[PDB]
Image 1 (cartoon, protein in one colour):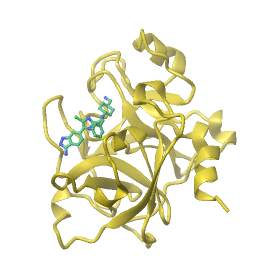
Image 2 (cartoon, rainbow, N blue to C red):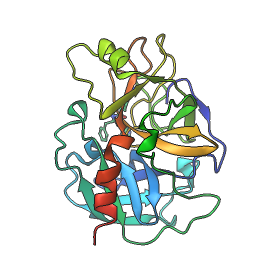
Image 3 (cartoon, rainbow, N blue to C red):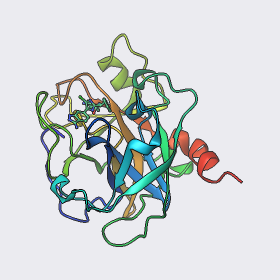
Image 4 (cartoon, helix red, strand yellow):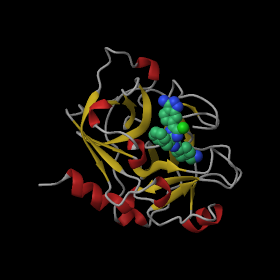
Length: 238
Ligand SMILES: NC[C@H]1CC[C@H](C(=O)N[C@@H](Cc2ccccc2)c2nc(-c3ccc4c(N)[nH]nc4c3)c(Cl)[nH]2)CC1
C-alpha cells in the first residue's frame, strides 16, 4: 500500500495473508474470509501454482513477524479459479480457496459481508484498501498491515485512464486523480472494503493497475457484486 498507515490489530479481521511454501516460505497475496472454510482472492495469484499443498492461509495477523514455523495456519483443500479467467487485465480475476479446516470466528478473524444484488446502485463513499504490499515501486513486503482510504471512480472515468484497455462493468476502479494513495505490489487478492449503513462490504478484490499511486492511474479491482452468483454457485454447491 502506497501512502497508507499501519492498521490497528483487529481492524480488518477478514484480511488474510496467503503464503506459498515453494521454493521458500513468503507472502504471495492478500485474501478475505467470506465463510468459515472460504477465502476470496485473485485468480492471478495462482500463476504457476501447481498444487494447493504449497499454500498456507494465516488469519488474525497484524504483523508478518507473527509468522514462524510454530504459527498455526489453514491448509488449502482446493483452489477454485473462475473458468473464464485468462489474465487480470481481461477480468474474471477471482478465485476461492476452500480451507482444509474451519475458521473459528472471534475478534481477530471473522467474515466480511459480500455486497447485495440490490446494492449495485448504492454509492460507496467510505472505501479502504489494505495489505502488506510495497509502499513504493521498488520495495519489499511490509511487516505491518497497511490501510489507505481511496475514492471509487466511475467506469467511464476509469476507462479514460486506461486507453488501450477495456475496463468492463465486472471491474471497479479506485484512486485519486493526483495519485498518492493506492494498492501496490503484494496487495493483490486482498480486499477493497467499503462501509455502508455501519456494515463493511467486500466491494473489490485488488487486481491490477499501471504502476502504484501514479496520477490518473487508479487501481483496478474485481467488481465483487458482479460475482455474487458465481461465489454462491461454488460455496453453496449441493
Ligand atoms: N496499483 C495497483 C496495484 C494492484 C495490485 C498489483 C499486484 O500486487 N500485483 C501482484 C501480481 C502477482 C505476481 C506474482 C504473484 C502473485 C501476484 C504482485 N505481487 C507481487 C509480489 C508478491 C509477493 C512478493 C514477495 N514475497 N516479495 N515481493 C513480492 C511482490 C508483485 Cl511484484 N506483483 C500491483 C498494482
